[PDB]
Length: 108
Image (cartoon, rainbow, N blue to C red; front, top):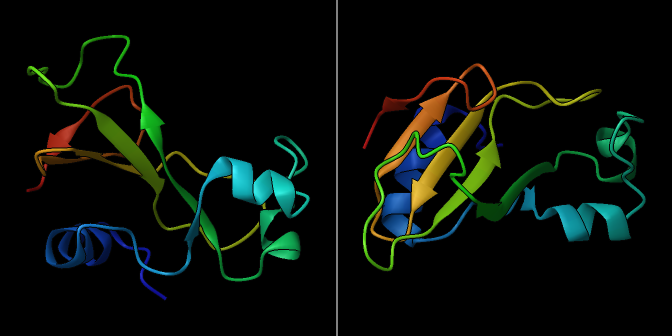
């Protein structure tokens, strides 16, 4: 399973998509995930949430003309979701956060 910061970042850069263990929130809900129940690993064994649009409401990440952002959960195994996320742009800037989008560090 590829779910680490470097592992997913390099996969994104090589393939321009997330590895096969990622599903979007709509897909997880279709499988029976309910936010707050912490049941993702029971309804979708070995899957992590990722691929949904990150809005960047707080302007913390660089904006550009026609640049949009997506997010993916990192280091997820089971139970309630953590605070680790990879946030990646349409032009392939890649940032990490370990505090649920409070702070960011550029890694690609």
